Length: 301
Length: 301
Image (tube, rainbow over all chains, first blue to last red; front, side, top):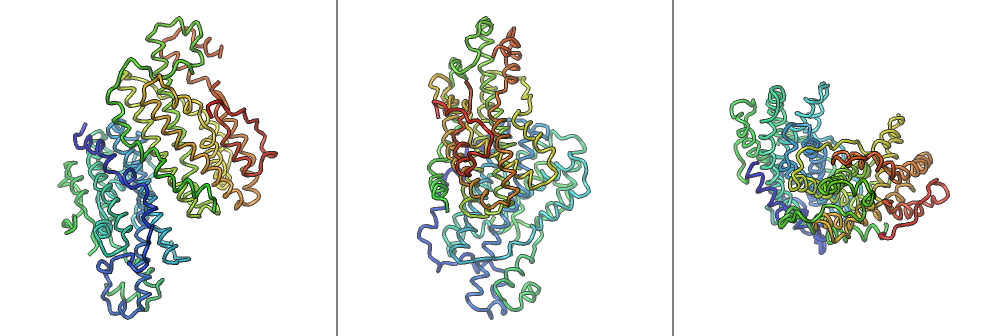
């Protein structure tokens, strides 16, 4: 099979977050409240005069709410979008998906996503306890998921449903959230927050390459109509993931009690790294077939 | 909160198979064909004259097929029975399930089961390759899963379906396969086969305790009609897992080409350790209310 796939599979034990930092709970050991939860630097409205007009404790509440929000959306994306695409591959619904190397690589990724959910849930649970947050609004359905659920609405054919689920998961795993890399590299925020994002980024870097490899091999074995449908839904999913939703922002701002939240969000760079998906598209021989305009590779990538 | 739960959560990092034997795939490194896959000592028809009349290679195909059969049923059990009950706990439908300690303990078990699946899949893949087994049906739908789908098909009400899932999952995680314990301690079979089962047994012992605490905690928060539904389906589930099924062994004997297989099967202990579910029943205070005769806990327990 793919030598690259072979490598990623053999490398998993020494790379994986679950193997090498199972004791993440312990990282809250000697917590210090005075370190912030989220970097002000990457807050798009950090210097909006209405944000500066607020109380220092309101600004901190916003920083904290954005961190928690970030975590909630990571868990939702994984559970609703990424894992179901991995689960379909393991279920053998695609020809060539019975290959023992494809199955090994994907099942390893499933173990990782299980651990990612665990780390992010612990992040939320520990932040809430330690910052004394009794009840915040969890509320909004992921926007990416809403868009996916609309695609599937008028789609009776199971084989076509499966292509869509596979594509949405592939995009999700090959387009890296800006906040993942930015939080990973930040030395000003809580050490466990930068740790968790660092561990997650290390696994996700691997998942991106696995997906490029797996999708190429599956596209190769798909019938003509599966192939066309894959190329069809690619730009849709890609546009869904390129989209920025300010709606999350408004809610946090309003929650921390900041006056003129609507003007801040109105008056208002966190672009995903699409490089993995560019690589995926190219490996399909579709570097002329997909109606999507790839954002130029981000500086942190 | 439950002290036991607190315990198992803190111990998970040093206990979990995924942390301590993630490089299980390397374990095929010095493979020796001469060592059997399965212990003749625990094969029920090992001393049957018709099985003794077979050619040596045919006895070996049977031993190997039973090992593969075992692994296939483990994966099916984890994916169709156990995981869906853990997944229901995490998605919040039961009152009290929002508790952070229950969430930590169950998400840890989810990570474990992902890895159990990985280990068993590898076991099959490596066996098929090395024993040069190219064609084989996975064939029969799980008997316990068939029984489950039967019970579910006549439930129009989602809340009732939820109880059955939970309970079926609960019984699966508290009633230990004899094969799991018998293979773990066997010094005569391939060392990876006894390794895989030993690692899975370590994790499964903790899962049974977790499930006892979680179930008790969730039963307490349930409404009256949920209480009743849990109590009613417990003996139904216990019976499925107590049920001996001979159908798979028949296929193995036929696949191997053993003459008089039917008569060997018709002529035909592998009882689970129900001690875990015994403790669960007593933790619910339900000793008088469930109609099930627990077997005397096995020597290996």
